[PDB]
Image (cartoon, coloured by chain):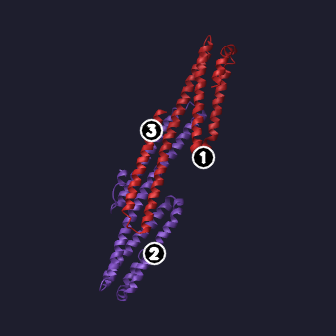
Chain colours: A red, B purple
Amino acid sequence: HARFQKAKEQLEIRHRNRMDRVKKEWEEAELQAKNLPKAERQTLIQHFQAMVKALEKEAASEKQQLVETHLARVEAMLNDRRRMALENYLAALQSDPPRPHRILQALRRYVRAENKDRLHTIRHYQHVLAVDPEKAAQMKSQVMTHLHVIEERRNQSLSLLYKVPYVAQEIQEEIDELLQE
Amino acid sequence: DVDVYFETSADDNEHARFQKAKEQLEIRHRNRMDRVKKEWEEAELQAKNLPKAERQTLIQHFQAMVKALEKEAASEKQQLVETHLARVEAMLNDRRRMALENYLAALQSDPPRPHRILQALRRYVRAENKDRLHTIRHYQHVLAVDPEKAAQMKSQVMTHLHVIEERRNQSLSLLYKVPYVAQEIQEEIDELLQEQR
């Protein structure tokens, strides 16, 4: 997250310096053309305007490359941590005999990882909602489906506690705490 | 390479320098596009054991990545074109202005030499033809690759062609104020005025 925040800052600076430089150069070109007819001055300014629009399209495009690269990496980290937390939960659930509090530890790490997947999904989606309504509209179906998969994955892991009903009551209140975020 | 083009003053080698900078940009973008495509595909490989929905979101990011890279390329390409067009237009306008001045000056000289006026009129009309031909040609280029962008600039293309035609006819009408000269080069004038039709 920090590495992305740092590249994001360098990108904004880079975009600012370039926008300022090009603007200053083209305006310098407009000054040298102050003695030219009104029509020649307009088409030059029109070129400057097209120049600005291409620069803004370039800037947004480079920002999108950063974001797509960032999102993919975060999703990889969230999916991998969840996998390892799930394995440790299964292994602790199959141990002989099963100690209810080593299982509680493993269940905590898994459920909280799912919450972290949940938190990142909602946060990024709300971010897109605030700045780009149509992009949010496009990802809307997939956002909901993923949140539903997280919920199913949760309940699915919890259903494994039914297969050991005794342990489930010895940590029922901690589980209820965990489930209340 | 390409960046140097933007800080190189227009001259007679502007067109060539632009053509090579245009080519270097297309190559650099393809090289960048290829490198990135390879990297993400390895990430698609490393995620092959994942559920079908999770690989979809990864592939979907790659698609969004390609779309961003293509927007970056076209954007950098348009910057090149806008810079080039301004440079060509300034050289064309300066050449027309100098030729029109020499034509006016030759027209008011005492006495007016009919072949000095002809010589000057040739440089002007041919400068006007170079502007006209450039306008049509760039338009055809945009038509060939981006029909929708061409349709939007068409109106300005037509107006620019109209101004050229107006400047032409007005400059030619000034020959009526010098009845002697106009008769001795009428046939040269008629040839000149039909050039590049």
Residue in the picture at 43% in, 62% down: A44
| Camera sees residue B47 | no
| Camera sees residue B180 | yes
Residue in the picture at 34% in, 82% down: B107
**Same chain, labels 1 and 3:** yes
Mark 2 highlights which residue?
A: B165
Mark 3 nearby-residue class (10 Å; few <14, some 14–19, many ≥20): few
Instruction: Answer left or right for B135 relative to B100.
Output: right
Mark 3 highlights which residue?
A: A7
Q: What residue type is labelled 1?
A: Glu
Mark 1 highlights which residue?
A: A134
Q: How far apart are marks 1 and 3 (CA)?
A: 25 Å
Q: How far apart are marks 2 and 1 (CA)?
A: 47 Å
Q: What residue type is labelled 3?
A: Ala
Q: Where is residue A37 in the image (x, y as percent from the top left)?
A: 41, 69
Q: What residue type is labelled 2?
A: Glu
Label 2 resides on the chain identified as B
From the image, which quarter does the C terminus of chain A lie in? top right
Q: Is mark 2 on a helix, strand or loop?
A: helix
**Same chain, labels 2 and 1:** no
Q: What element carries label 1?
A: helix
Q: Position of residue B158 (x, y in %)?
A: 50, 69
In the picture, residue A81 is in which quadrant?
top right
Q: Position of residue B131 (x, y in %)?
A: 41, 69
Q: Do the residues labelled 2 and 1 touch (CB within 8 Å)?
A: no
Q: What element carries label 3?
A: helix
Q: Are marks 2 and 3 in contact (CB under 8 Å)?
A: no
Q: How far apart are marks 2 and 3 (CA)?
A: 53 Å
**Same chain, labels 2 and 3:** no
Label 3 resides on the chain identified as A
